[PDB]
Amino acid sequence: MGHRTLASTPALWASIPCPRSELRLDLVLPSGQSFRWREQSPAHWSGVLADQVWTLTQTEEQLHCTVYRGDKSQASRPTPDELEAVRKYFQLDVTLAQLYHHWGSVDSHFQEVAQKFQGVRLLRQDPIECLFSFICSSNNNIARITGMVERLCQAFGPRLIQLDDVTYHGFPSLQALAGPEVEAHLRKLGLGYRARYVSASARAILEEQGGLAWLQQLRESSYEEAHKALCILPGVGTKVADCICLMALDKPQAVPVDVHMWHIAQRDYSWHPTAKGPSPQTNKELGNFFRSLWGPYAGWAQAVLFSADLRQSR
Ligand SMILES: O=C(Nc1ccc(I)cc1)N1CCC(n2c(=O)[nH]c3c(Br)cccc32)CC1
Image (cartoon, rainbow, N blue to C red; front, side, top):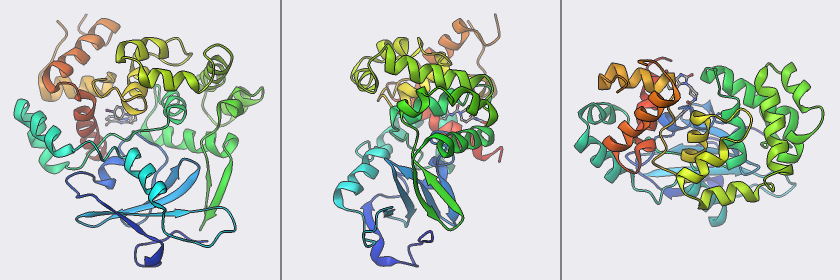
């Protein structure tokens, strides 16, 4: 079985109405939200959504989707149900045009970046995948996070399918990551101190917080409650808790502050603390600065600027 292109198997592609103004796969899938997507052919992005492999590509007005099923069933277009899982993952019910207008109307620098970086949306990620991917993100570059997440899934996620050279795994279950061998094994895969954070956080969610049920509860809770609750987990500080809140728990006002948002603040917003250096208090101020500027979807605005900085550094 090989990776499909819109050309190589036209009958196996289904279409979502979706202009490039609303979504640019090339500016979203490698922009450090999800670490699971690869451009395996020019303009074709392959990765795992909900334990199935997809390839996505786009024309001017359409998002084209194809799904590989690891069963013995005949190949077929995505069902309307499967298509809806893609629509929710890209949060296409949120119209980017109105947000881009608001952010540009209050912020000249954003206006400037936004011209070049259209269609940068926030993915709605699975909370487990989002939590453990960003535990892997601490003191780490995008290349090394992608590698660490890839090795974690290979080791502890179910094998789905092989396409050309690439073997795809689902994201590990809590049960898999709570296992007794996990920590040692993750240290062998170069996760370092993060190996223990993964094991201990999987055990803390299963044993103390009542499993997956908890992350659904946080999804339905306030930003303030969700952020506080996440911060009890080993390896989850303010930055990682904000990433999870923004990317998996529907808190669009979350502004994850680390060195990267500091660099944008100083370089592009001539910003200083009101200790001149990254601390809890100065990190909190910076987050409040961008919520005050951009409004209730501040974290979506940040995603645009992060997409730009990531692209313009390789
Ligand atoms: O912080 C995130 N992701 C993230 C994406 C969107 C939102 I909103 C919030 C966080 N992580 C993945 C990207 C990673 N990173 C680099 O390695 N270089 C970066 C540059 Br240049 C600039 C911004 C991040 C960078 C840091 C860890």
